[PDB]
């Protein structure tokens, strides 16, 4: 015969929390993944 | 900037404008200072008629923007040099450019307490916005942000 089991609680409680918690043992890149790669056009860097 | 000027000048023949600007520039170099940008503008129509050295009121005047790095001692000399020149109608001076109004008020700056080097690097144009600026620069700004932050170290650690 079956019964409801009481789920033993998770530490973090959500996946997003998982990523963030994992992320303090890591080094953020200065640039996000989609702009790291140089553009196909060329941007001449001026002063602001 | 460290210092800036707005110079309202009399609209003369070009050789004269060039001589006068060479005089102000040389007056800045002799005193051991630098010119970030000398920006030219056109002959405009101001809201107030200015009288020149001839005491003849003028409807039009040429506007010229100076941006300087000096010591505060010897810009007294450059000040009374510029104001005493005959081709300058008016000069207004901005000394507030290193600590402008919008910073360092009740911990408004996040992750730093009054970093002075933020506004020194900048030119006057980005501290004080001109009227034509629209939401469009919010685009350009970031392409000039991200791009910059990509190439900086690699460019610097070359030599």
Image (cartoon, rainbow, N blue to C red):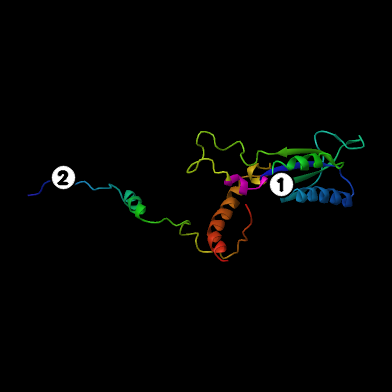
Task: Check the residue under mark 1 and report the chain it is in.
Answer: B
Count of all numbered marks drawn on residues in the image? 2
Q: Is residue B107 magenta?
A: no
Density class for disc 1 (Cα within 10 Å; few <14, some 14-19, many ≥20) is many
Name the residue: 75% across, 50% down. B38
The label nearer to you, 1 versus 2, is 1
Residue under pointer 1: B67
1 and 2 marks in contact (CB < 8 Å): no
Name the residue: 82% across, 49% down. B21
Q: Is residue B119 magenta?
A: yes
| Residue A4's disc number | none
Residue B19 in percent (x, y) is at 86, 51
Q: Is residue B3 above or below residue A42?
A: above
Is any atom of residue B53 visible in this view? yes
Is any atom of residue B136 visible in this view? no
Task: Check the residue under mark 2 and report the chain it is in.
Answer: A
Between B88 and B34, the residue placed more toward the observer is B34
The image quadrant that residue A44 belongs to is bottom right
Residue under pointer 2: A6
- What secondary structure is found at the residue carrying circle 1? strand
Residue B102 in percent (x, y) is at 58, 37
Q: Is residue A23 left or right of residue B62?
A: left
Q: Is residue B113 above or below residue B159?
A: above
Give the prevailing secondary structure in the magenta stretch: helix
The span shown in magenta is B117-124
Residue B154 in percent (x, y) is at 54, 63
């Amino acid at each position: 015969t079956s019964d409801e089991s009481h789920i033993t609680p998770y530490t973090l409680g959500s996946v997003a929390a998982g990523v963030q918690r994992l992320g303090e043992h890591r080094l953020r890149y200065t640039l996000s993944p989609w702009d790291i790669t140089p553009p196909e056009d060329s941007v001449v860097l001026k002063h602001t | 900037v460290f210092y800036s000027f707005v110079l309202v000048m009399k609209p003369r023949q070009r050789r004269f404008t060039s001589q006068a600007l060479r005089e102000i520039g040389v007056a800045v170099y002799s005193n051991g200072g630098l010119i970030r940008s000398i920006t030219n503008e056109g002959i405009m129509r101001p809201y107030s008629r200015f009288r020149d050295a001839d005491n003849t009121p003028l409807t039009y005047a040429r506007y010229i923007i100076l941006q300087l790095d000096m010591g505060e001692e010897e810009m007294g000399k450059v000040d009374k040099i510029i104001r005493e020149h005959q081709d300058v109608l008016m000069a207004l001076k901005l000394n507030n450019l290193e600590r402008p109004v919008g910073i360092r008020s009740g911990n408004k700056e996040l992750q730093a307490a009054y970093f002075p080097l933020d506004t020194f690097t900048r030119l006057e144009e980005e501290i004080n916005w001109s009227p034509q600026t629209s939401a469009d620069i919010y685009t350009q700004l970031e392409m000039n942000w991200k791009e910059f932050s990509r190439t900086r170290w690699s460019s610097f650690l070359r030599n």
